[PDB]
Image (cartoon, rainbow, N blue to C red):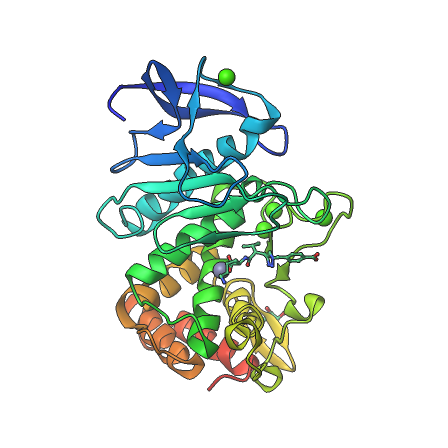
Length: 316
Ligand SMILES: CC(C)[C@H](Cc1cn(Cc2ccc(C(=O)O)cc2)nn1)C(=O)N[C@@H](CCCCN)C(=O)O
Ligand SMILES: [Ca+2]
Ligand SMILES: [Ca+2]
Ligand SMILES: [Ca+2]
Ligand SMILES: [Ca+2]
Ligand SMILES: [Zn+2]
């Protein structure tokens, strides 16, 4: 909508207060004009038609409980925008400042979130399994990273390329969480999963096995569920990425960690310059090696740590 840029205030899902960029034109809309061609958050109103109505509020204060998922969806899209711009020099998900749109209050008691090819969608959770999923910055960045991948490598959402697609989203979801630096970890979705159970999550990058995900190529799922297990076999890549950053010994294979930022530079480059829609695991290894090479030199620790990590998860 056409109107004047302003700043609203409200509370997110976890009860935290934050300012949000809005647009005024009779009502205050969740439209952020300070980032690229804009960040727009919508109300799906418990239904599934998308995107719904551009979020509208009479007084620019968003402290209702109904407001919280939109507050966080909107704010964390902005944070994720900032990560990609400041850290990888990338403008929005298409690299050309595409408008970022999100809808919240999708369906009823919907325990999930997703990128539908054109926008982010967030359920409110059933309240026991999940709380509104936009309360999770790793979730928000996971979903926007799916748009990044779709505009770059275009990894097909099936089998090994689909597992890579997933890992990429968990990896930058996590790097963005660290970036915001609020209770960061290598777990996914912990902030909005099972409010009544502390310490769990949907997936663990540091120890995928925690939730039954493989942490080695010899443990890969080869059935047809989950698109050929894209959320399952992603643990093999998540584990490699964790090792590259943090280091460790895994099934007897030692990795020297090079830290999060270099992990991020290497995988961003692999994603945007080498990976293709049908890249498999072994191809990912060669892309990451070439990326590390480009960035740090063939003889680097960096290159050597990337090899160690993939050796440790059995990917040659
Ligand atoms: C953290 C978050 C990003 C997420 C987690 C997620 C949510 N669900 C549903 C779900 C529902 C109930 C339980 C339970 O323990 O009772 C667990 C999981 N399964 N996985 C997830 O990974 N969602 C998918 C959804 C889009 C997938 C496209 N097919 C994705 O973004 O890849
Ligand atoms: Ca209000
Ligand atoms: Ca966290
Ligand atoms: Ca996390
Ligand atoms: Ca929990
Ligand atoms: Zn995903």
